[PDB]
Length: 67
Image (tube, rainbow, N blue to C red; front, side, top):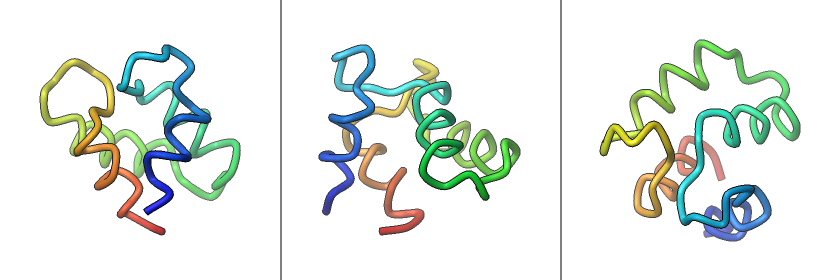
């Protein structure tokens, strides 16, 4: 599962969590077809802890949306 690997490359906050901002830069950068509504609906949907960022377990499910 290259979901953590891809996250490392995006860990722009070396925090172990991404913001819809990193996943939106991630989504707009590699998968530009991702509509901001699909990225935010899903990110808003995957960001389960509500910290406003993709956590590690959700990170893999954040990528499971593909990969």
